[PDB]
Image (cartoon, rainbow over all chains, first blue to last red; front, side, top):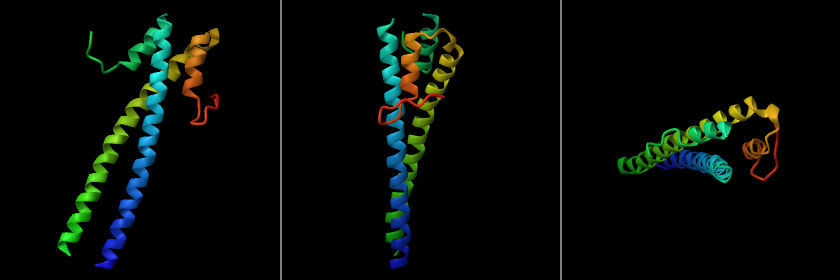
Length: 62
Length: 69
């Protein structure tokens, strides 16, 4: 019983550390895209339009 | 205990679903930024101030320092 709890709690602790690092990385990249999205809206250029297409590549609106 | 393993298996199974969902989100965002970086690299010979601002966002660390590539 004690050995099983020891193994699973160590596995859970490892998964939760990887989850925290992955979500931190996800929010880090999402912040970059939103700041780039802000720059494209301020300067609303054929180069910027290609960047806008990437930002909303999977957007079905409009 | 069979009810102890079930308590920990379903918890690990829950965390692995969260990991798979987060990794898909990160790769989605990182793929966009990588495509944006390549567009800026193809047009860097003009020293466009707007594109340089975008590059400085791509290459900024979490402390705010820009590491060029």
